[PDB]
Image 1: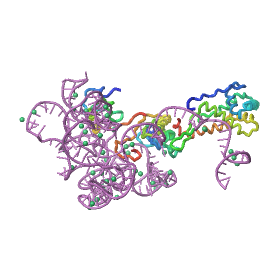
Image 2: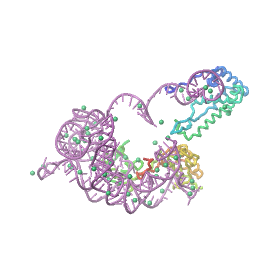
Image 3: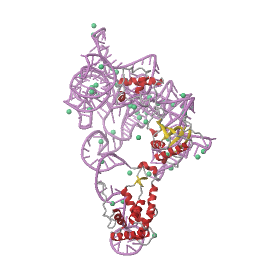
Image 4: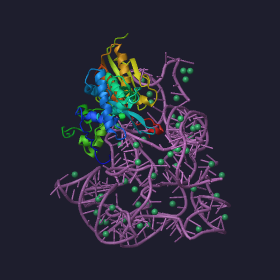
Length: 155
Length: 70
Length: 116
RNA sequence: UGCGCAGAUACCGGGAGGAACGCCGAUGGCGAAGGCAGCCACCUGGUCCACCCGUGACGCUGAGGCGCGAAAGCGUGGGGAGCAAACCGGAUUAGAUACCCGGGUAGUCCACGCCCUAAACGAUGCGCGCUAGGUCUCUGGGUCUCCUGGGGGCCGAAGCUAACGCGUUAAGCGCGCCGCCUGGGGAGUACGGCCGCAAGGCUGAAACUCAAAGGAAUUGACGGGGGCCCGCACAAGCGGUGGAGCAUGUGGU
Ligand SMILES: [Mg+2]
Ligand SMILES: [Mg+2]
Ligand SMILES: [Mg+2]
Ligand SMILES: [Mg+2]
Ligand SMILES: [Mg+2]
Ligand SMILES: [Mg+2]
Ligand SMILES: [Mg+2]
Ligand SMILES: [Mg+2]
Ligand SMILES: [Mg+2]
Ligand SMILES: [Mg+2]
Ligand SMILES: [Mg+2]
Ligand SMILES: [Mg+2]
Ligand SMILES: [Mg+2]
Ligand SMILES: [Mg+2]
Ligand SMILES: [Mg+2]
Ligand SMILES: [Mg+2]
Ligand SMILES: [Mg+2]
Ligand SMILES: [Mg+2]
Ligand SMILES: [Mg+2]
Ligand SMILES: [Mg+2]
Ligand SMILES: [Mg+2]
Ligand SMILES: [Mg+2]
Ligand SMILES: [Mg+2]
Ligand SMILES: [Mg+2]
Ligand SMILES: [Mg+2]
Ligand SMILES: [Mg+2]
Ligand SMILES: [Mg+2]
Ligand SMILES: [Mg+2]
Ligand SMILES: [Mg+2]
Ligand SMILES: [Mg+2]
Ligand SMILES: [Mg+2]
Ligand SMILES: [Mg+2]
Ligand SMILES: [Mg+2]
Ligand SMILES: [Mg+2]
Ligand SMILES: [Mg+2]
Ligand SMILES: [Mg+2]
Ligand SMILES: [Mg+2]
Ligand SMILES: [Mg+2]
Ligand SMILES: [Mg+2]
Ligand SMILES: [Mg+2]
Ligand SMILES: [Mg+2]
Ligand SMILES: [Mg+2]
Ligand SMILES: [Mg+2]
Ligand SMILES: [Mg+2]
Ligand SMILES: [Mg+2]
Ligand SMILES: [Mg+2]
Ligand SMILES: [Mg+2]
Ligand SMILES: [Mg+2]
Ligand SMILES: [Mg+2]
């Protein structure tokens, strides 16, 4: 984006929860243009999480996402020879994309056999504060506050 | 900002012993203020410099001070 | 073991390091910290973060001697010269005054090639 | 590398010693040039203005001569803080006989005597006379919006210049006098001479060789120059190739 702001795409509300965040999550699950597959994965996982735990799957999806959101990360900046790992804050938009992506990529590293099983279980773990997604978030937040000495390079 | 000569009376530019007036021409630190701030002429500043230095050797005006800020 | 409760804190700020000494009102030191005192070793010592942590280490070391009132003297220019002061203010030490006393010569001594 | 537990760095106090003068400070001043910045006093040179007083062409230039002459360097004796050729290390690097970092001798300072070079530059010899102005400034005098001298700047008339530019501070118009140039390389070399303790300076060729050497300006290219700005160029992101088997094209054989 050299000219313009490259406005954000406006997703369609979820056919089920009327909620956009859900649609985006489905989009990150979808592979090779199979959105029907991805949606059936997500919703069957909603049954899993709503049964194995007696709470609304909506609130757990939001909470699980919310606990993966990183508030700070690190970015390289080329300074006087070799570049530096430089901490700075994370755009709310970027917190969004990173948290959803991390959730999906973590769920597929799970031992569970079926997709919606992994999705449900990772959603539950991440909503409780555990699970691999929350570890990528905790590791990134460890990257900041470690290279904190470069907080003057903010840019 | 007003200038020093503007807010001042008829004073002897050569009197090195008058501290009350000379102290008006030093900065917060002991430095000599440029003509832009003193409003003196080329000749007048040339004379003030010497009389201030004479007064500094007498222990009347300082060579340098400490900045209380920042 | 002294109970001064008031004194001077000297911020020596160069480009390669920032180091803080804390003395009684007669100038005699009590405790001190620096960029190398806290973990940092190399270039990282002259950073403003290391200035913050050095200032705070020395301020906590002053607490045990009872320091509350502190007058700050500052010599030198460099990163984290300001950051050390701002750390000195929120250190819990009440900062009485701040002075810059950085020594400048009247063109007396020939500097190294680096400084011409 | 170096220094620090024999206690450094940082801080306060006392003392020693050498060198240079912050602010003022200027696009400023002075000087024949080199050059001259804390302050006081002594000795001392130049220069400018006002009065229109005195002498009555006593003037200008200037081959030789003589004096001066930044830095570095030379001799003797001091001195020696900081810096710092050479040099000792540490790094970097393909190498590093360097740029960077830790040290360090001469020297940098003083006296006295040498040396005599320089981008010693305004790359513009000195003196006089004539040729629009405007503006900034330093310093005199005046009846003190200003007028009138003497310096230092910037625009610019006429004019000059190849052009850049110069333009009452001439590179314009004139006159006097001195110094100097005559294609590039060889070469500021060789020889002789004069001078120097030395290093070296002043004077200063030839054989040979080349169709050039050069000045200013022009369009363009380029910059590990500047400003501004585009492209899936980077970045953000998603899927790949590089690995396997095979298809196919190429190199090689
Ligand atoms: Mg350092
Ligand atoms: Mg600055
Ligand atoms: Mg300098
Ligand atoms: Mg040791
Ligand atoms: Mg050791
Ligand atoms: Mg030892
Ligand atoms: Mg002392
Ligand atoms: Mg002394
Ligand atoms: Mg000594
Ligand atoms: Mg100055
Ligand atoms: Mg007469
Ligand atoms: Mg007569
Ligand atoms: Mg003459
Ligand atoms: Mg002669
Ligand atoms: Mg000489
Ligand atoms: Mg010399
Ligand atoms: Mg000598
Ligand atoms: Mg000697
Ligand atoms: Mg040294
Ligand atoms: Mg060295
Ligand atoms: Mg070496
Ligand atoms: Mg090596
Ligand atoms: Mg190389
Ligand atoms: Mg010169
Ligand atoms: Mg001529
Ligand atoms: Mg004459
Ligand atoms: Mg003029
Ligand atoms: Mg007048
Ligand atoms: Mg002059
Ligand atoms: Mg004039
Ligand atoms: Mg013309
Ligand atoms: Mg002109
Ligand atoms: Mg005339
Ligand atoms: Mg003329
Ligand atoms: Mg000409
Ligand atoms: Mg020839
Ligand atoms: Mg020569
Ligand atoms: Mg001969
Ligand atoms: Mg000879
Ligand atoms: Mg001889
Ligand atoms: Mg030799
Ligand atoms: Mg040319
Ligand atoms: Mg270009
Ligand atoms: Mg390059
Ligand atoms: Mg591309
Ligand atoms: Mg990319
Ligand atoms: Mg392939
Ligand atoms: Mg393998
Ligand atoms: Mg293959």
